[PDB]
Amino acid sequence: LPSGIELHNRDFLTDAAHLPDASIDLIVADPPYGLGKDYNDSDKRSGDDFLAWTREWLELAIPKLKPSGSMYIFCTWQYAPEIFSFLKTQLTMVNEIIWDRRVPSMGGTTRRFTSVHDNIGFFAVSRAYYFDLDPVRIPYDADTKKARSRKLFEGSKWLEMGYNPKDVWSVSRLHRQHAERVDHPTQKPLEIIERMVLASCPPGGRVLDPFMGSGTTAVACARQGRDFVGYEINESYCAIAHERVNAL
Amino acid sequence: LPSGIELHNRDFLTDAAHLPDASIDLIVADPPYGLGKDYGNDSDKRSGDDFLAWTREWLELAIPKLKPSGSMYIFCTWQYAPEIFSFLKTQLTMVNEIIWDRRVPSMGGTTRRFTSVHDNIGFFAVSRAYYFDLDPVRIPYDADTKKARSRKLFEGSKWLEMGYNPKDVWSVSRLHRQHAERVDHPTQKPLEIIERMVLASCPPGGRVLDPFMGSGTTAVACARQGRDFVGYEINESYCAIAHERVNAL
DNA sequence: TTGTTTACTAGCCA
DNA sequence: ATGGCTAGTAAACA
DNA sequence: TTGTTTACTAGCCA
DNA sequence: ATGGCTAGTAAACA
Ligand SMILES: Nc1ncnc2c1ncn2[C@@H]1O[C@H](C[C@@H](N)CC[C@H](N)C(=O)O)[C@@H](O)[C@H]1O
Ligand SMILES: Nc1ncnc2c1ncn2[C@@H]1O[C@H](C[C@@H](N)CC[C@H](N)C(=O)O)[C@@H](O)[C@H]1O
Ligand SMILES: OC[C@H]1O[C@@](CO)(O[C@H]2O[C@H](CO)[C@@H](O)[C@H](O)[C@H]2O)[C@@H](O)[C@@H]1O
């Protein structure tokens, strides 16, 4: 395991104290959504119970942010207004990013529009948070270049280097047979996590994942060169995280 | 003006008495986002608690106008969506959170954030027996995509042979100024998405309310789809365009 | 071209 | 207050 | 092929 | 407390 890469198979809430306050540049928080998934009982909480537990781990993770830190939190629309409304009292919301998973959730419903997107709250401790777009700009290919280029835009940073990813990221969910896929139920694309890691944490900086699971953020910090602290209570997920960071 | 489509050049929050309680099948509300736009008025200049109290006020007037099967779509920005949705969940139940991918991002010149190309829409319902019909809004596959999707497991399926759910993310590009449908409105919404709402959550003949009709896109939607419509808008210029868009059908 | 699957069925009736 | 039966649900990876 | 624009800069300075 | 100046921000309509 590399320098700065820390994998703790420990309950984050008990072992948060073991992490120094104001010592993490970025928190990549993909916690249980409260959707009844089989991880333990972590995602088997619903309603005000789940909201209370969410707040409980958030008040432990927030103080560990440096004055320049930022945070991305994954959630479902079913709870996003409340969790975001709470986090707006503690930090400032810089963005709401929509992961358009392209592939919709199945079930067989016809009484509503099917879920295709996940909500991501992008918060910051202060207005002097760190944000660097250049590493995450998306380049135009030759054809997309020739289409967007005009003598009003020639030389513009968005044209030559790349455009802003925007607050909706259209990336397909990892198929079970995808090369990236491992033995985790709710994996996250490396594209997404890597974008966030590059855009809000200095090189060699510290990224905390209170609910790390497969080490997706761990892999994202291994490459791109950033320090990482992870917390996953499931032994098998920590194993797969190790294998994922020990193959780069 | 056609029958069943009513256009009012007044303030909504004050004519709410006129509207009967439990008469509206569907509310399609596109309110001021609290963003500083100039609608010819200063309604979108409110921010923070001012904006949110004003929002909750007009909402407390609009909600009783929905009959039990009633539903509501509400446009908003991510800066105020958590609070607005949190309040509305105490009144009605949230069925969906639809994200309007406007495809074209907001301009300004920032490099410290992610440019906006999403608007939030809250889909709430009064009861669990709310009206909803997906078949009018199913998206049919074309001769190439259905072929790419058709497997023996899916042959004869409702979603394959007819059309799939539009999902809670609608990637409909914003209306360019030179676009044919575009009128002289600062924040015009495309006819596609409002027509989708009108077709799905309002039965043929039902009454739709747009407290902030603007250019009357909901009026055109209700006229083209055989649904009654009522609207409110203080700008007479916007109401004039709202008219013209309906008489042109 | 094809098997298969991913964080988000639901309304009745009993 | 609580299950079970039903008609039903996409895009994209290997 | 090309002009033009649409609900959402941002920090500094005199 | 107030503009102004800067360095910038894109898909898609006509
Ligand atoms: N108290 C807890 N502390 C640390 N991890 C937890 C805790 N409770 C649940 N978890 C784990 O958090 C993970 C949530 C996952 N959605 C994270 C997946 C991860 N983002 C990935 O891309 O693979 C689950 O695997 C849980 O086992
Ligand atoms: N009290 C008010 N009552 C009725 N309309 C109002 C009020 N305040 C502001 N408005 C208008 O509400 C509209 C908000 C816009 N989103 C309407 C756009 C409209 N959905 C369209 O299709 O273009 C503005 O045109 C306002 O002038
Ligand atoms: O608006 C529904 C919304 O509420 C949530 C919590 O955000 O669930 C709560 O409210 C439901 C109302 O239908 C109850 O069924 C549920 O018991 C309660 O927790 C979400 O599940 C849903 O998105």
Image: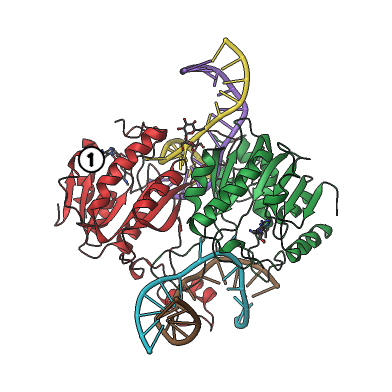
Chain colours: A red, B green, C yellow, D purple, E cyan, F brown
Mark 1, chain letter?
Answer: A
Residue B119 appears in the figure: no
Q: How many marks?
A: 1
Q: Quadrant of the N terminus of chain B?
A: bottom right
Q: Position of residue E8 (x, y in %)?
A: 50, 66
Mark 1 near ligand 1 (CB under 8 Å)? yes
Q: Quadrant of residue B164?
A: top right
Residue type, label 1: Leu
Q: Where residue B60 sits: x, y (%)?
A: 61, 43
Q: Residue B115 placed where, x, y %?
A: 46, 65
Residue drawn where x is 80% and y is 50% of the image: B6
Q: Which residue is mark 1?
A: A13
Residue at 34% across / 65% down in the picture? Answer: A127
Task: Tell me the crowding category of disc 1: few under 14, some 14 to 19, or many 20 or more residues within 10 angstroms, Cα based.
Answer: some
Q: Quadrant of the C terminus of chain B?
A: bottom right
For the point 21% across and 36% down, the residue is: A235
- When the figure is inspected, residue A64 is found, relative to residue B160, above or below; the finding is below
Q: Label 1: state its secondary structure.
A: helix
| Of B144 and D1, the residue lying toward us | D1
